[PDB]
Image 1 (cartoon, rainbow, N blue to C red):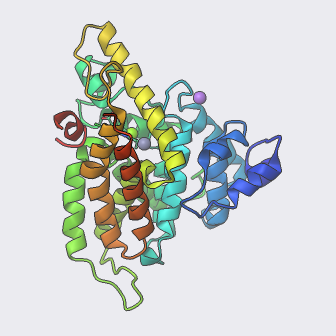
Image 2 (tube, protein in one colour; image 1 turned 30 degrees about the vertical axis):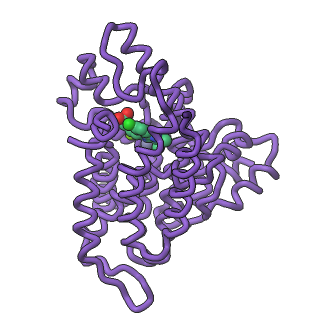
Image 3 (cartoon, rainbow, N blue to C red; image 1 turned 90 degrees about the vertical axis):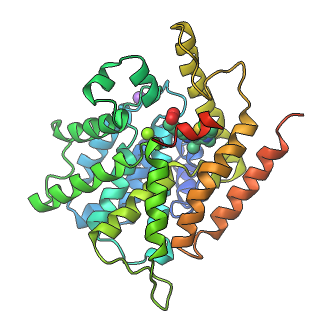
Length: 345
Ligand SMILES: CCc1c(C)nc(-c2ccc(Cl)s2)nc1Nc1ccc(CC(=O)O)cc1
Ligand SMILES: [Mg+2]
Ligand code: NA
Ligand SMILES: [Zn+2]
C-alpha cells in the first residue's frame, strides 16, 4: 500500500481508481484526499514521481521521498480553509498535466520538469491563511523579515528548502552539485512568480513572449534557451495556481467556498483589530457570484487566453470550461479596484 501509493489507505481500490485520472485535467483531488487518509499531497506527489520515473532519473530514494513529503504536507495548515495541502496537491497535479501539453513535447529538461513539480508542491507551505497585504498592514514579523516583497512566497521557499536539511529528508542528495544549484534557482524563480501581485506584469511579459512564438510543422513550440523555458515554467505554475475556475463546476464551486471562507476568516481578524476590512474579506457585504465573474473576466480568462494562444490548440477545452463556469456564476448573481489590486503593483 505504502509501496503502491506512498500512503496507508483503508480503500486501496477506490484510491487506485481515482489515480487512473492522474494524467487528466479531470482528476478529482478531493476524492484522492478522501481515500488517502487526508494525505493528498504525499499521495499525488508519489504518483506523479512514479509516473514520470523521476525517482529513477534523479536517484531519489522512494522512502526518503515519502519522509520528505510527509513532513512537507504536515507543514501545510489543516485549519487554513484554502491554502492547505489539498491546494498544494492540486497545483502539483495540475502542473503535471500542463507539462504534458502536446505543444511542449520534449521541450523541457528532466531537471526542469523536476523543478516545476517540486515548486508546485512547496509553493504555499506554512501559509498562515492571511494575505501578504495583511502581513504588511499588521506589521508582522514575516513582513519585517522580507521587506514587504513577496513575503509569503519567500517564506514558502525558505520552509521548503529548510525541510531538505532535516535528517532523512534530503531527497536531492544524489544530484550533482551543478544539478542542485540549477534546481534551486529554478524553484526560487517559479515560487516567487506565484506572488499574485506580479500577475499583471507576468502576463504582460508572457504576451510579449507569445508574440514571438514559433512552432514546428507538428505544432511543437521552439524555445531558444533557458530564459524562454523558465519563463514558460513560471507562467505554467501561475496558471496551475489559478486553475480552479477551469475545472469542472462541481470542483470549482468547492474551491470557491474554501477561498471565501479563508478571506472571511482574515476579515474577521481585521474587524477584531479595528482595521478596515480588506476587499473580498467582509462576510456581511460579500457578493460571491459577482466577484467570481469579475475574477474570471479580468484576471483568469486573460491569463488562460494567453496560455491557450501559446499552446494552441491544446488548451481550448480549458477555455471552454472557464467560459461555461463564468456563465454559471453569472446566472447565480442574485436580483473593481479591490479585485484588480490583489493582482498588480
Ligand atoms: C483560485 C481560487 C480563487 C478564487 C476562486 N477566487 C479568487 C478571487 C475572487 C475575487 C478576488 Cl478579488 S480574488 N481568488 C482565488 N485565489 C486567490 C488566492 C490568493 C490570492 C492572494 C491574495 O489574497 O491577495 C488571490 C486569489
Ligand atoms: Mg501563494
Ligand atoms: Na497539517
Ligand atoms: Zn497556491
